[PDB]
Image: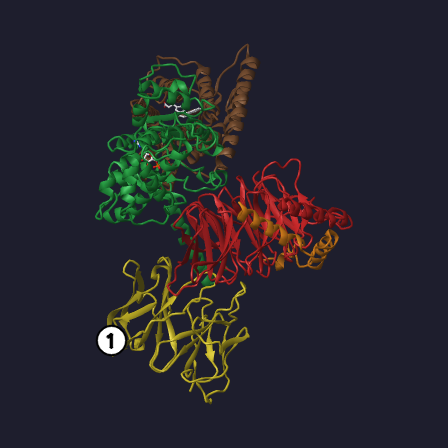
Chain colours: A orange, B red, C brown, D yellow, E green
Amino acid sequence: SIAQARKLVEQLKMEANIDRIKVSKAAADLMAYCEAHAKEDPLLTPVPASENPFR
Amino acid sequence: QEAEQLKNQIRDARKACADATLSQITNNIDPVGRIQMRTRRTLRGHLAKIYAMHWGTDSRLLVSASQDGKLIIWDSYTTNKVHAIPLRSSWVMTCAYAPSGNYVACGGLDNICSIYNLKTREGNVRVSRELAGHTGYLSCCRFLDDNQIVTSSGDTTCALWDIETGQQTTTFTGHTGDVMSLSLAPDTRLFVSGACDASAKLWDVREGMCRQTFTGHESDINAICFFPNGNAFATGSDDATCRLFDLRADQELMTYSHDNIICGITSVSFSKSGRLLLAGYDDFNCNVWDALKADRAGVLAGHDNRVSCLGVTDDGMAVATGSWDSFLKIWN
Amino acid sequence: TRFPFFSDVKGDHRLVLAAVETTVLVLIFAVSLLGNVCALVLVARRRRRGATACLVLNLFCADLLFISAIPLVLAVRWTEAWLLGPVACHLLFYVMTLSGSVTILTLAAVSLERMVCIVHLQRGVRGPGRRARAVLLALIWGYSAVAALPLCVFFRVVPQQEISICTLIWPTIPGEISWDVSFVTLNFLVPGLVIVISYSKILQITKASRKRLTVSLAYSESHQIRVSQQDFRLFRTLFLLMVSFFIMWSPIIITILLILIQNFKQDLVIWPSLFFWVVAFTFANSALNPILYNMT
Amino acid sequence: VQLVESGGGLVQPGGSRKLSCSASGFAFSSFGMHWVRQAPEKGLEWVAYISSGSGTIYYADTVKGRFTISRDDPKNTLFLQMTSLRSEDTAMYYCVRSIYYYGSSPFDFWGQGTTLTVSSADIVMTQATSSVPVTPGESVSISCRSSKSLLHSNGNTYLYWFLQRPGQSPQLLIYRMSNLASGVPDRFSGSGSGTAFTLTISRLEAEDVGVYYCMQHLEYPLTFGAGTKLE
Amino acid sequence: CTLSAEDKAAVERSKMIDRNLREDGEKARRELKLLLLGTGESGKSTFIKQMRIIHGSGYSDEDKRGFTKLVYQNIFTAMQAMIRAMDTLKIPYKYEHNKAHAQLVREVDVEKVSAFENPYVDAIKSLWNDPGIQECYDRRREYQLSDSTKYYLNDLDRVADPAYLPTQQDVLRVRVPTTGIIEYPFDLQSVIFRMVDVGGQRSERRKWIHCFENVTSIMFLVALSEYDQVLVESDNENRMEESKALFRTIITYPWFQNSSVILFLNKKDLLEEKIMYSHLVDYFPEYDGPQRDAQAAREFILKMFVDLNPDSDKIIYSHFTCATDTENIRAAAAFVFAAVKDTILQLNLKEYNLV
Ligand SMILES: Nc1nc2c(ncn2[C@@H]2O[C@H](COP(=O)(O)OP(=O)(O)O)[C@@H](O)[C@H]2O)c(=O)[nH]1
Ligand SMILES: Cc1ccc(-c2ccc(F)cc2COc2ccc(CCC(=O)O)cc2)cc1
């Protein structure tokens, strides 16, 4: 049990020492990527029928 | 006791960076609103439940696997069947299409991932390789390239295999329950994997070590995919809940659920810009959520049985949904 | 003189008999139309296009074509004479005979294909495929259009006081005898015998299988009163289908033979509205067929 | 991956000949087959086509009804029955393997052919010149023309560039005006506009000499040009 | 037809593929899939072995050469299990010297041994004939132990031969520790069957059981010897209760409402020899019948198991089998074929809106 507990402790240790960011920056990056490629999103912005490969 | 402390410090540090929520910062954007998609093509020919499909990287070809014991490669533009691959094991749960298009993968209850070469000089599709070494069924598989493939099994372990030698290059142990889904980062230097322990994990392909672990679902995580930038990923569980996890924030950001949705998600996928998350459900529907607000719910209601698989092209120009009524529909 | 069809003379109760007949036939038309259209909708949706799906949709098509002639009959009965013209006199009875022949032949084909598919699934072997179904439907409609040919060439409007009646003029008595006998024997007796044999064979196979399992021990200590209901239910259903076919298709055959006898020996007299009421009972077939063949 | 023709030879005026092709090492029942002529002092010429599954058959308007293509999949043997052989029928006849799905490279593998010596709405493909003097190590470019535009409204352009080296059967270089066949060095490329096509070779090596052919597949018949001889 | 030549050829190929798929998928409906279920040590691997012997090609001598190593792992595993159960039931050895022999067996690498020579043979023999070890075998009731232990330790001398080759019975009574779904097809009177055996898969059943929605029938193997063993090697749990729980879980699945259930009650002979020592009344209070009778026990177990069926819309074919001796498994196979034909009958009658 000592070896099994030791391995679990190390995994918890390595995940804790991470330079995380705030959720606000993550959400901002999400909406920035979304608004950056909004015109090139065919399902979000229906392409004209002449330029549609699926009619 | 030290393990509890490490879990304690992580949780308190976890709550620190959750100063706001994705919902609060998205109250100043215009919704897309209703999105009316149409079955431009209905791909017919599968005779049993369809369990997985994968788009080609040309955004036109499409492989799909059924319990009829067969993969079918479709030309989605003309509803033409390009290839038909009979499987050795008919209990197939997953399939993959290589980025270069030369290869296809499949696997299932036989615990073996079979790779098939598509560009042969003999004119047929041969079994290039049979990767064996998992002690449970294979739930997903994804080509990194023509040479390496990651397979997730019910072993509670994933495995990165070098195909040309057939041996597990690396193994990813650490899950408690059966691993059910798998998604590769755009650069394929990472992958993300959810299992029947309600937790997903972000795994490093190169170093082979589990970087991150995401908790928050209440049942099996049986659908997972990346936001197109590779910094976020959306899970689908049996809770009738999808959820957005950002790797940098190390948290959960927004939930995708409704009061009238009681059945679990079978598949998730994003739109080319990540503004739409399509989610296949067990109520025979396929919802389309505004991934930034969680309140769009366009419906691709054309299937009469459980929607088991769906996917969006690499130009976001369409979306294929295969379901348990053996039909693939291409919505645009 | 010559036996009138759908043309009667109403006396002190002209507004009573005509009204009640119109009400009865409108009820039959409504129930048949709604039942057959909903049956067609629910059968065309199925992705397991077995023999039953295609043959019952043929059945519902036949029923709709059969009831498509209700309003004309209402017009003839209400106006007490024929005014619809030679085209209607040549089309109405041909369409009714066509649809009745198709409906009976389709009941026979449904029973036969049910039994044959049961036998082939018991043997686990190949059977009649899609081509067989297409050939069967084509042959049914072709035979029902050929055997009904006289009833478009031998219906004429005759001034028989002299009033216009859409009656039937057989050129020769032997031809009338032969057509009536052949129609009856190959559109009521062969299909009926097929239905009886097919459904009794189904029941025999089921009972044989139940015996072959009950010789093991008993299936259970209690399930012998959980299987015996299924034998009773199957017997009830198959016997109901047989007797329903015979009871709701026998009066029209009897009246056809009565019209033959009257047009053979003028001694016998047949009531004027007896034919019409037997025709209404036959029209009830187009309503009760989707009931029996889509019970659930 | 091997096609062997048989049955060619000297025939009496008139007469008939059955030419066979044995396929070995591939799925010949999943491949369409072509018969392609070549005169002893002229370019290639398409004879016929049979489909994957024997569904459809195509002849040229100089042999139609006088020929017959057929196949036998269990023994993987293709047949051309040939009747009433006039003088214009003395040519080498090659059997070409050709598959058609999305992405296939038709005409990729040719047989070795067999000699047979006998004792206007079609698209017109036209070579620029019969030969091009060159120097080893240089960059070379030949051109070819078509009466119509081979750009079908589906986005494809069904031009094909073939190489026939001296003493060898042809060999697909370019399929559909731009795409390099498997095994062809990357030194080759093909480009142009509708009704104007150019084949370019960079770093011209030895054994790259021969005759280069510009065929079209937009419709049947398939029309060749004379083909430029790079010497 | 605006299609070009190449797209017309592509359409041709797609139609060819359509025809091939239709052919293969109508072959895939003449073959009836029987999902073989049950608990561990209930007798379903021996069941598939038996029908392979009487409907497949049987086991050739090369297969026996492959099986011999598994046989030796079985002999070592059974001996080690008895040895461990000796030290957990608090029973001492009548002979002290054999205790050392027992130690010689405790450190054996079961998964690695491929040779079976002295002193291991002599140590096993001297352990088995100990009065204490015989008492432990008699009292094997309270711990896990393969039923084929008597059979192997009373032919030790035969299996210790340098030229030993497993026989058909040895092939029957040996575990093949393979993981993964195993499909095995059959020809029963020109009807293609396929027993799908799972349970070698240690993963969660709920995640792959819907894959068997399209099974003709479920062959559930219950072992009639599961009573009179509340194993003390772990928490006190009866094995009959585990079998009943699994039966309820299987017959409440919505996937299996279209599929009949064939219940096979197995290990009947071992019930016959257990009745002469142990009676049902000690473990099942609802039972009320003769003490030294076997048919009463059999019918009590069947009545107890068939009444777990929640509804009257599912009939449970049942059989009393002994999946070790042939000419009884032939009767079981005939019963399976008959029950499957009856299931097909009832499904067709329900589809035709008759049953
Ligand atoms: N005496 C006897 N032993 C049996 C019978 N059925 C099974 N066994 C024994 O029980 C053991 C366990 O059966 P197995 O095949 O291991 O069952 P599984 O655990 O469901 O795969 C077999 O190896 C046989 O030795 C039976 O009817 N009689
Ligand atoms: C099988 C079947 C099906 C449907 C119907 C049916 C039903 C309603 C109706 F109004 C008319 C008909 C058919 O019309 C006839 C009228 C007169 C005769 C008399 C022949 C002589 O004896 O000369 C024969 C036929 C009959 C048989």
Report the front residue among B254 and D56.
B254
Residue B66 position, x and y percent, is 46, 47
Chain at numbered mark 1: D
Q: Amino acid at mark 1?
A: Gly
**Quarter assignment of residue C247:** top left
Dot 1 beta carbon under 8 Å from ligand 1 = no
According to the picture, the residue beneath numbered tag 1 turns out to be D9
**Quarter assignment of residue E194:** top left
Residue B203 position, x and y percent, is 58, 55
Decide: few, some or many residues near mark 1? Use Cα within 10 Å; few <14, some 14-19, many ≥20: some
Left or right: D224 in relation to C32? left
Q: Classify the position of ligand 1 by quadrant: top left, top right, bottom left or bottom right.
A: top left
Q: Is residue E101 above or below residue E7?
A: above
What residue lies at 43% left-to-right and 13% top-to-bottom? Answer: C271
Q: How many marks?
A: 1
Report the front residue among E157 and C71.
E157
The answer to whether residue C252 is visible is no
Report the front residue among B255 and A6.
A6
Residue B33 position, x and y percent, is 71, 47
Residue B185 position, x and y percent, is 59, 57
The answer to whether residue C41 is visible is yes
Q: Secondary structure at mark 1?
A: loop
Name the image quarter holding the N terminus of chain B: top right
Residue found farthest to the right:
B28
